[PDB]
Image (cartoon, rainbow, N blue to C red; front, side, top):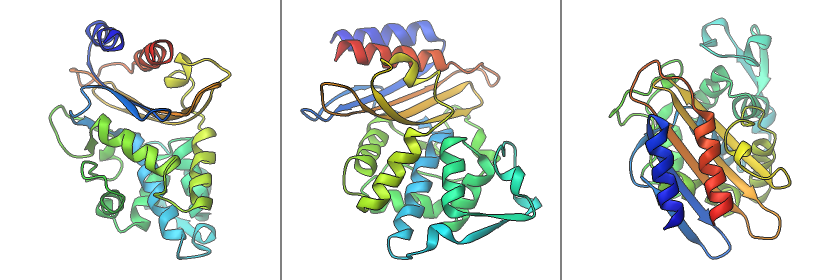
Length: 261
């Protein structure tokens, strides 16, 4: 299709490997580019961890409000929120907000630990029907995206389906789904990524991801004016370990989708 050719041209220009999955909920059509290839998730996996803790909270009433100690051994490589609470506490809701809206890596580690380790995040994915997602590590090593390493990967097709189920479907209870959407809409890290390719009057919730090999990711639910919501996953990774981030490539993918579908 025209969109497919434009995404191939984008990838050709980009210096890396591009993965796209778009679901248009108006007719449930899907557009994929490398949609069944595995890509390193990096920080986009924070959505699955936050959603898994929200699922826990459905049967543990006050779980999101219990204090979690932030100890010095907990601090990792990027802790814009948690470093302000060392030797103090943060609640699981505060940790989820920090992980999702600031991409705080210590916060995500606390979420992973609350779920019983990386396997607990993967188990939640399986429980909601995602057979592809795998989380294998914590931070700091989650920031590493070696080419061909299956750890901490998913496919664009699988992540788009999961993101749809979590935000628009029934994977979470109503209060939890609304909370997840509220957190994603308040992301602070995404302005140069999918959001930069979309009209400003459209509402977006998203989670970016970044890692080495110039890995630059974004997963988003989009509420355009005048049509039903869209789910868009854009994954991008490059051949050189020290490649520079390419949020602009994700914005181009979003622009191709916004203009062409």
